Length: 135
Image (cartoon, rainbow, N blue to C red; front, top):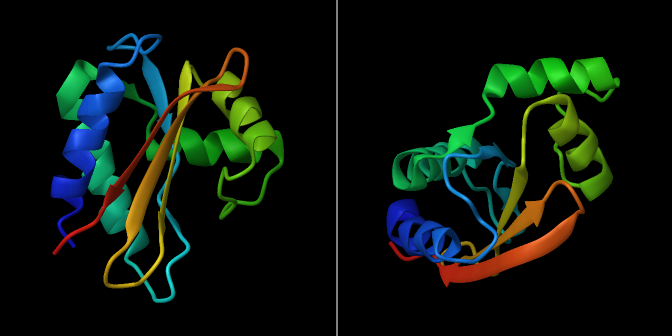
């Protein structure tokens, strides 16, 4: 999985979208696997986390911060912040201005990485991107 090759142009496209100020606080939801096979969850998420940190100078909400915030919210420790409600409530508790969603779908050897940037304030999807994950 060339996560990088798939993820850098998307992060780049998102950085150029109006409404995305860089250097702001961003909640990076971890990559959701909807392929027909097992994918290394956090291998992707970390590549993502690095792509977003380096490019566009984004302040990412940290893993520990995420953990403690879900606890303070009463959510399960392994809870994924998949539902928007749970994602803003978490986002508000931390300092986040944007929640980033991302999913890998289709065939386990030809996934379609999709991506949406949610404006925490209003909950509107202001940007969306999709790109194949090559090898």
